[PDB]
Image: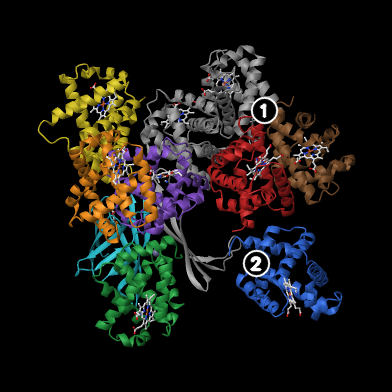
Chain colours: A purple, B yellow, C green, E orange, F cyan, G blue, H red, I brown
């Protein structure tokens, strides 16, 4: 169960029906839902976001943060057919997450689960299996060198 | 089976591999690349160099070693081109495993290393290189070749 | 299912795919109408003013388009509850006084839910559409 | 197809259940058992109206 | 003064240049090629990402990050709160590096030079400069 | 004909029609309940499958659309000649990429 | 629905409730228990006693009040035995709610109290008493009976 | 979502595959894991368990403590069909926890979460939903009269 | 002197008496019935838990706690560190109450009297007294 | 998955359920063997000494039992890494010199992972078993 | 053959042996018992301890020796469970005899001693122990294992 080329092409194709707009509203709503799920399942992680004002989920800071995530994921997926560049960006994102203490691999497994829970609610014909097989690949690279 | 070295994975690998051999002196390039890979392997794991004594690795510019680099590169080319036909590929790779079994001193760790070296080199020479597909497939290929090794 | 924030987003996207490209829009509309009138032919009397007897008449075309426009505002504002409430109140006012049995709204729903997958032909969710339609229709009724 | 009669766990009245065989795998190296995949459907007349309760299963 | 019609226009044209993945990469790379060609004084700032070699993976990943952030800001152009938050976030990512504030004008210069090659429409230079400046102003101290 | 995406990579596929529901108020797009039956015998095992699926027939396009029943984006689409009706071409398509990855020639049995 | 007063909950409740009525003078026991519950309720919430004026609560040993204790105990017995059939139970409980609505002065607080009293008594008389199941179910039963009360 | 009789019977049945032995090894391992999780998510609580040498966690003292917990939970579960006795033991355990200052209800919600995270890792066919629904019942009684 | 085979035997027989939930409660209750029958001088100590009424919930819960602790100690019989720790923990739970140290011998007496009724095997009295004493010794000061 | 402390505990418990009751133990063993030899029949030549040609022979029964005993020591010591390492080294020595392709170990794994759920029939985890088997097999190979 | 370790003898032995391994930490018990037997053998006949140098007997709580105690206990368990099938038992015991032959220094007297120690320990741990049957059978088992010893 690796991340096949078909899986990557699939994800790339379905991706423009999950958010993707000249406006950030869908990104905010969906990413927001992903984190509501994450915090519901791993509430300890919610403390890691006070810098971006999780306590006030309608704040510009938190919105802008969600958009930062969404666009980060966008960047990752867009790089699926450019493995070298994907590797560099993956490393970059990883270090960005190492600077933040308290962020664990377990939290990443968690967010994978919440993504998998949220995406099929916002778009039909979303290949969940493909998503899982590929996310494992992305996260395992981002979240290595973090506390287990 | 699918997912790990899938159909499209194999298509990508073949298409990208095809880029290297454009001109009439493909032999020169195969020899150069094979020589690079092998000598790099002998540097990384020094105990390996002795295993190539019968192909005159001490004179890598020499005849015998050049012909040998052609041997490995052509085996690699063959196995890549055979990825359309899994059964035939499996048979060829099995023959290779047999051949590497008859060379005592060859170990799986050597194949792990040569995998690393191979991917590192291919990232350079190939302008378009899908690491996911290549690694997915070669895990299986090199796996099968090293499958009959004692150590 | 129920009209979540999420499933509302899904319905919204699918409605974009179905309605937003004014090509077969009047035909989409008219298909919905042929289905509705096929289920409850007695309802044609409510549309005398707008030529319900002939759904190919320009007056009825204009009508069905007005409808789909209203419904479009409703769907488009599923994620903007204030605006949604506003449009729903407006539609409700436009519909009060007219003796419309739940019967007819079920006909409308069934029509929409058969023409929609014929339009999209692909990835669509009849449960989400059922939920959100129920919300909008409840809004129009009271 | 058959009638399910509940007397524990759930508080359902008597109702139809279907076991729908969807696939089988029988390894030639282990024929002692057949690995079955199936869909379990139940017609529940829960709240005045009828509703299907189905799930995917394996064994 | 980046008004409704301005930001709407910029949003559209941006969608033209960045919304298609088949020429997004060419777009980024050419933006950088131009920038570094006409202002090589700038290249020193990008040693961390091989700015001397834009055809490298390091720099490619960089340019990708750039265009992504630019996408975020252009997309938040209508949400003043989240906009301000995002622009201060960009500020934090740039303030640590001693960046000549008039380099942003040059960046805009390269952007406007490269853009029409990826636009099926005529570049609205007014809208673009106005919005780009309402972004850069926030990035700068 | 060709095939590089289906799970079992079978020689042949039997499509069995089980039921047809035609809405009186929308007769142009009948709904079918069909089963996709596959029987593949490899070395390691023998696999048999009967996948219940929902389908729509489009008179407009002379086309059967069979929605996937398993957890892959794999749908079956049968294009009719317009005049034959005892033979269609069954293309297997990723519901998402729209990529055409398998084709079978179906005949009425 | 399940979890709150589940199937097994109901089975437990019925099985344990059955223990009380072993012999032929079950009427004596029902009257005693009902009289206990009711007079205790009238003591705990004194405003209640007036509501039973028409059944002669001032003479709890008397005919009318005894017959009445039989009324409540039999309604309770019926509702317990009806827990197999949720729809019929719901209908019977609804009839009870109607009956208690037609008695102005009856309030939900009275039902909360009688719930407490009931559970306290049952803990004593029953040798085997699963409080979780009993409370789970009676929350719903007494809930439904008090559902049509003005206060 | 209460704690049904079925849930209790379920838990009682599955319980003999999670630790339960004439030897304490499994109890120590599993309970130990539960607390590793707890402290990972609510590190402030780790300060309470010194007396028991939380700090050196191979200390006969800490082992014996873990075993005390495991056996306490055992006692609770075994009393699921004896509600009166369960109530008394629940009260007893509660007071034992009131004597310890710094122990909050939040810490109890936390340990519920960590139990729910650990148990399905050590035994298959463990009914997680049942466990949650019943634990809520146990903890809410133990941890009332404590501070949120 | 509670050696390997001793503690192994005691572990097994204990599993017989306490490992089955259907007769664990009868076991505890009968242990107490016997103890209080043959040494009513002891009952004063248990006023906190209605020792005068062993059929009460208070005392039931008590006996349950007892058997639980006894289970812990018997189970820690092979882990000397954790054993000592557990036995000193039991000590702390008993030292506050003025308990005649020869009451433990009586407790063991009742235990040995009740045990064979719940053992499908023959009671190994030697092993049981030896291990019980290596426990009580630690409980006492 | 990977061989956690926890999933090791799980595997250990399930192995208890499957192996510890010497009733059908030789039959369990032999089932494993029939499956293995069915997958890779060429491997029978490695077992000439112990009558691999007839898995019902007393010599081969004795064999398969020796195997399951070794594997039992390995599983039983998953939570005692020193002892585990010891037993794995021992098995490795017993296996070195014998030309055993990874092929055959995959056959063994597949055999075990089909006979196990047939034995337990109920609550079992093929992923945990996959992980821990991989650990033990890697130990035996080197 | 019959009389000496008969069918019923074997049934008794198996049934009684089964009592030890009730719980999930049977490994702990096997290691404890094996360690006891072996160290006791090393005390009774001191020349023996040297023979277990390769399994680190000097650290009996250690890994290697624990794994080894599991080895012997599992061999014993296996041989007991194999008493239903005399031919298979004979084959397994023969393999064991081979294994003990390859350890020079192992003598029949050691097996006599370990027989004594074994029976003495089993009398304690087992609550039900038919010494006649056990000794009848183990005379043959231990006999066969020590049958290929030089001394
Ligand atoms: C699903 C893969 C994930 C992606 C693609 C992602 C993306 C991002 C991005 C783009 C940023 C902004 C960095 C910057 O602007 O410099 C960020 C920051 C951060 N991430 Fe993630 N993230 C992921 C998963 C996680 C997980 C599982 C955690 C654990 C809770 C986490 C914890 C954080 C924290 C604490 C920050 C700091 C934000 C701030 O303080 O402003 N991330 N992430
Ligand atoms: C990268 C995948 C590899 C391929 C495709 C490959 C292919 C070949 C081929 C075709 C031969 C010729 C055998 C013959 O015709 O007689 C050969 C020989 C040999 N290979 Fe490799 N090989 C690979 C990796 C390795 C590595 C990792 C080692 C470890 C040192 C190794 C050790 C040897 C040795 C010692 C010979 C003997 C050559 C001789 O003396 O004639 N091979 N290989
Ligand atoms: C949620 C689905 C529906 C929507 C969005 C909708 C919306 C509308 C709209 C936009 C108009 C135009 C009013 C105006 O601009 O003056 C209208 C009029 C009307 N609707 Fe609906 N409607 C719905 C369902 C129905 C139902 C089920 C019936 C019962 C058959 C119905 C009966 C009518 C009638 C009789 C008129 C006025 C005809 C005229 O203009 O003379 N509508 N509705
Ligand atoms: C409004 C136009 C601009 C946007 C949207 C933008 C956005 C970004 C983004 C998203 C990053 C990556 C943040 C990170 O490290 O995670 C970045 C980094 C950087 N930017 Fe900009 N930027 C802009 C203009 C400029 C200007 C004019 C300069 C001056 C040449 C500049 C110099 C740099 C440098 C030196 C870095 C970090 C290099 C590195 O990552 O090693 N940027 N910018
Ligand atoms: C424990 C659950 C209860 C049950 C099963 C129950 C049942 C009954 C029944 C069967 C009757 C006879 C009505 C008739 O036959 O016409 C009755 C009468 C009555 N109940 Fe209850 N009851 C319950 C709780 C309560 C409580 C808490 C109150 C508050 C004081 C209450 C107040 C009354 C009153 C005022 C009457 C009228 C007496 C009469 O005129 O005969 N009930 N109840
Ligand atoms: C899951 C329900 C819990 C049970 C069944 C349980 C069980 C126990 C037991 C049996 C003791 C031993 C008391 C004694 O023998 O004197 C104890 C002590 C203690 N408990 Fe818990 N516990 C639970 C949850 C918690 C929680 C969530 C916390 C908050 C961190 C907590 C904090 C403590 C502390 C600080 C001690 C003192 C230990 C000592 O000083 O030796 N407990 N618990
Ligand atoms: C080795 C045998 C014994 C064991 C394992 C044992 C264990 C225990 C345990 C676990 C408790 C509950 C601790 C608590 O929560 O406070 C307890 C309480 C108590 N024990 Fe023992 N004990 C033993 C022998 C005795 C003896 C011989 C006596 C003298 C009659 C005794 C007198 C008491 C008393 C008076 C209490 C507390 C009563 C209360 O809480 O109201 N125990 N014991
Ligand atoms: C992890 C799974 C395996 C375990 C636990 C295992 C364990 C054992 C054990 C305990 C012995 C007995 C040796 C002795 O008593 O001296 C043995 C011998 C042997 N094993 Fe394995 N083994 C495994 C997998 C395999 C594989 C896959 C093969 C390749 C077919 C293999 C080939 C052999 C052979 C040929 C023998 C000796 C046969 C003889 O005595 O004539 N083993 N192994
Ligand atoms: C109680 C009956 C006995 C049984 C069931 C038994 C069984 C075993 C087993 C299974 C092994 C492991 C061999 C291997 O896996 O390589 C072994 C090894 C050994 N046995 Fe015993 N044995 C018994 C009695 C004895 C006696 C009386 C002696 C005399 C000291 C002895 C001396 C040895 C020695 C020295 C080893 C060496 C193990 C090594 O070096 O790895 N055994 N035995
Ligand atoms: C399907 O294919 C197999 C050969 O691949 C054949 O034996 C079987 O009869 C075929 N069925 C039909 C109807 O073609
Ligand atoms: C991520 N934040
Ligand atoms: C290899 N050459
Ligand atoms: C609607 N008309
Ligand atoms: C910005 N680079
Ligand atoms: C009440 N009666
Ligand atoms: C809590 N122990
Ligand atoms: C002690 N009781
Ligand atoms: C394996 N022998
Ligand atoms: C014996 N060893
Ligand atoms: Zn069907």
**What is the x, y in percent for residue A137?**
37, 42
From the image, tell me which residue sits under label 2: G140
Question: Could you tell me how many numbered marks the image carries?
Answer: 2
Q: Nearer the viewer, residue H137 or H148?
A: H148
**Is residue I58 in view?**
yes
Furthest residue in direction right, as rendered: I41
* Helix, strand or loop under label 1: helix
From the image, tell me which residue sits under label 1: I81
**Residue B123 in which image quadrant:** top left
Q: Is residue A62 left or right of residue G21?
A: left
* Image quarter in which the N terminus of chain H is found: bottom right
**Is residue D35 in view?**
no
* Helix, strand or loop under label 2: helix
Q: Is mark 2 within 8 Å of ligand 5?
A: no
**What is the x, y in percent for residue I101?**
84, 32
The residue positioned 38% from the left and 46% from the top of the image is E88
Splitting the image into four quadrants, where does ligand 5 fall?
A: bottom right
Mark 2–mark 1 Cα distance, whole angstroms, equals 53 Å
**What is the x, y in percent for residue C17?**
30, 64
The vertical placement of G73 against H132, above or below, is below
């Amino acid at each position: 169960d690796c991340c096949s080329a078909e899986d990557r092409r699939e994800i790339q194709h379905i991706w423009d029906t999950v958010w993707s707009s000249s406006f950030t509203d869908r990104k905010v709503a969906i990413a927001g839902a992903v984190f509501k799920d994450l915090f519901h399942h791993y509430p300890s992680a919610k403390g890691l976001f006070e810098r971006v004002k999780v306590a006030e989920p309608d704040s510009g800071e938190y919105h802008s943060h969600l958009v930062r995530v969404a666009n980060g994921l966008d960047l990752l997926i867009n790089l699926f057919q450019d493995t070298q560049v994907l590797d560099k960006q993956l490393a970059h994102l990883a270090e960005q997450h190492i600077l933040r203490k308290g962020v664990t691999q377990q939290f990443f497994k968690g967010i994978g689960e919440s993504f998998a829970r949220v995406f099929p609610q916002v778009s039909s014909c979303f290949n969940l299996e493909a998503w899982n097989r590929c996310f494992h690949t992305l996260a395992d690279r981002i979240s290595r060198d973090l506390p287990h | 089976h699918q997912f790990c070295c899938s159909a499209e994975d194999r298509n990508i690998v073949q298409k990208q591999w095809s880029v290297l051999w454009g001109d009439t002196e493909s032999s020169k390039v195969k020899i150069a690349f094979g020589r690079l890979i092998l000598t790099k392997l002998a540097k990384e794991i020094p105990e390996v160099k002795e295993l190539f004594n019968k192909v005159d690795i001490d004179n890598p510019e020499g005849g015998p070693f050049s012909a040998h680099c052609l041997r490995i590169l052509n085996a690699l080319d063959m196995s890549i081109n055979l990825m359309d036909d899994p059964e035939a590929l499996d048979s060829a790779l099995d023959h290779l495993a047999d051949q590497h079994h008859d060379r005592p001193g060859v170990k799986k760790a050597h194949f792990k290393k040569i995998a690393e070296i191979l991917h590192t080199g291919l990232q350079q020479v190939l302008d378009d290189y899908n690491a996911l597909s290549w690694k997915s497939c070669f895990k299986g290929i090199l796996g099968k070749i090293a499958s009959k090794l004692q150590g | 299912s129920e009209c979540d924030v999420l499933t509302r987003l899904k319905v919204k996207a699918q409605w974009r795919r179905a309605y937003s490209h004014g090509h077969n829009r009047e035909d989409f509309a008219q298909a919905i109408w042929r289905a509705l009138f096929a289920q409850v032919p007695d309802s044609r009397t409510l549309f005398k003013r707008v030529h319900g007897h002939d759904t190919t008449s320009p007056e009825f075309q204009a009508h069905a388009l007005r409808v789909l426009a209203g419904f479009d505002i409703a769907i488009s504002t599923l994620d903007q509850p204030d605006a949604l409430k506003a449009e729903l109140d407006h539609l409700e006012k436009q519909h009060e006084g007219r003796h419309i049995p739940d019967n007819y709204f079920d006909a409308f729903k069934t029509a929409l839910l058969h023409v929609l997958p014929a339009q999209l032909g692909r990835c669509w969710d009849k449960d989400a559409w059922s939920a959100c339609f129920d919300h909008i229709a409840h809004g129009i009724k009271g | 197809s058959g009638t399910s009669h509940w007397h524990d766990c759930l508080l359902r009245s008597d109702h139809v259940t279907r076991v729908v065989i969807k696939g089988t795998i029988r390894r030639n190296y282990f024929k002692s058992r057949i690995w079955v995949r199936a869909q379990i459907e139940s017609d529940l007349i829960h709240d005045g109206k009828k509703e299907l309760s189905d799930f995917d299963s394996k064994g | 003064d980046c008004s409704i019609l301005e930001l709407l226009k910029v949003k559209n044209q941006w969608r033209e240049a960045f919304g298609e993945g088949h020429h997004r990469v060419q777009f980024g790379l050419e933006l950088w090629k131009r920038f570094f060609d006409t202002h090589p004084e700038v290249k020193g700032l990008f040693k961390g990402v091989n700015g001397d070699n834009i055809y490298s993976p390091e720099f490619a990943a960089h340019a990708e990050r750039v265009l992504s952030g630019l996408d975020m800001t252009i997309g938040l152009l209508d949400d003043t709160n989240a906009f301000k938050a995002q622009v201060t976030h960009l500020h934090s990512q740039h303030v640590e590096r001693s960046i000549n504030p008039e380099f942003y004008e040059h960046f805009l210069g390269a952007l406007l030079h490269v853009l029409p090659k990826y636009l099926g429409t005529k570049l609205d230079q007014d809208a673009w400069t106005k919005c780009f400046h309402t972004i850069a102003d926030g990035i700068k101290g | 004909v060709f095939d590089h995406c289906t799970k079992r990579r079978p020689e042949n596929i039997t499509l069995s029609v089980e039921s047809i529901s035609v809405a009186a108020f929308f007769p142009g797009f009948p709904k079918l309940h069909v089963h996709v039956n596959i029987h593949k015998e490899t070395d390691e095992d023998e696999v048999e499958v009967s996948l219940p699926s929902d389908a729509i027939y489009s008179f407009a396009e002379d086309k059967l659309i069979v929605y996937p029943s398993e957890d892959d984006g794999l749908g079956l689409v049968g294009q009719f000649d317009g005049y034959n009706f005892d033979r269609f071409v069954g293309d297997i398509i990723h519901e998402a990429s729209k990529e055409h990855c398998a084709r079978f020639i179906f005949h009425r049995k």
